Length: 287
Ligand SMILES: [Cl-]
Ligand SMILES: [Cl-]
Image (cartoon, rainbow, N blue to C red):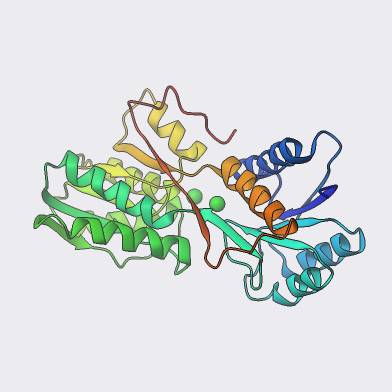
């Protein structure tokens, strides 16, 4: 029943997506043995290219497509062509219009977890800032989860949460610099991803400010470098995504649907795991 799978992701070279492809291959092997054909392509973050890739998978008569959408809404017609051909389409990491199932990390948990960690470390009192990012679901969920957690602690004061650091080091540097200029005492920093947190770390370094610690999100190699660094950093923790499990779950769910199971009505969320000084030596990252 499961003989071939087409996989299209943003960048096959990106360690995150390397892990996605590993997860697909491992789960395919688990379910159907060593003869499953898994075809991997990179969308290059281009909608036109990915539409073509989906149409190619349709002609090749794959049983399932694992889709990391270049454009969630724009890939819709292609997804529907696949489904009309009897192909199961499972979205990973981001939504894809019409996908039979969608698997992402629990980004809300990521935020709640990070900011519970901050609150606990601060013993439930102090000034905190949330360095925001692009207005996309994953980031917005992280912020929502974080804020809902901070609300539980009356002596935690959130000084800022609306600045968009663009998900980058450069943005995290710019935003944190402003926060440092405006706020003379910050006790904890939550950044919506690892590069943002690193940028904030750099801003602190340049300002000779060190009265806070910083938490990012993803458990990316960027975070590992900071957590394993011999030199100084204020970066102390990050909820890690598990792309390999996300991908294997995608195949597992897609196979169920292939076999006639009803599709899920809502996205399936993969738990995240807090990585810090206690488990960094143990952490199996994306590379
Ligand atoms: Cl990602
Ligand atoms: Cl960056």
